[PDB]
Amino acid sequence: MEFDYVICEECGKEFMDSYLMDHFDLPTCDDCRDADDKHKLITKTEAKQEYLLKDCDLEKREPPLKFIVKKNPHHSQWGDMKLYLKLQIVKRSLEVWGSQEALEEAKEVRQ
Ligand SMILES: [Zn+2]
């Protein structure tokens, strides 16, 4: 009868908003984490581009990855700001090359 909660589909954790479900559009909970201490997201520009990619991938299958977009929450607040969950951004960096080390090596090997 009328709800307003959600359970993390990753491991199953009721909740409503945290670091990804509070300003990202992704539920998750304070258990999956990603940075071991915060899961600090990663700028969408340094997330895919750096991961050797930029669109055409995360929109080719339409995965459960969400992003934020607005003034930065920490110090320094430029005009707009596009960010993408870091954990999910890592799952893709591998799905493509398979590891952030295969990326760093792909850019150091290529010209
Ligand atoms: Zn979870």
Image (cartoon, rainbow, N blue to C red):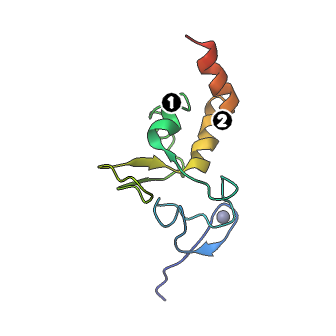
Question: Where residue 94 is drawn, which disc sits there?
Answer: 2
Q: Classify the position of ligand 1 by quadrant: top left, top right, bottom left or bottom right.
A: bottom right
Along the line of sight, the residue nearer the viewer: 25 or 35? 35
Is the residue at mark 2 in contact range of ligand 1, meaning its CB lies under 8 Å from it? no
Label 2 sits on a secondary structure element that is helix
Q: Which mark identifies residue 97? A: none
- Inter-mark Cα distance, 2 to 1: 11 Å
Q: Residue furthest left?
A: 79
Q: Amino acid at mark 1?
A: Leu
Q: Residue at x 50, y 40 (%)?
A: 58
Q: Position of residue 77 (x, y in %)?
A: 35, 53
**Residue at the disc numbered 1:** 53
Looking at marks 2 and 1 on the same chain, the residue that comes earlier in the sequence is marked by 1
Check disc 1 and report its element: helix, strand or loop.
Answer: loop
Q: Is residue 65 above or below residue 56?
A: below
Instruction: Answer with the quarter of the image where residue 95 lies.
Output: top right
Q: Residue furthest bottom?
A: 1
**Residue 100: in sight, yes or no?**
yes
- What's under tag 2, amino acid-wise? Leu
Tell me the quadrant of the picture where the C terminus can be found.
Answer: top right
* x then y, percent, for residue 9: 63, 63
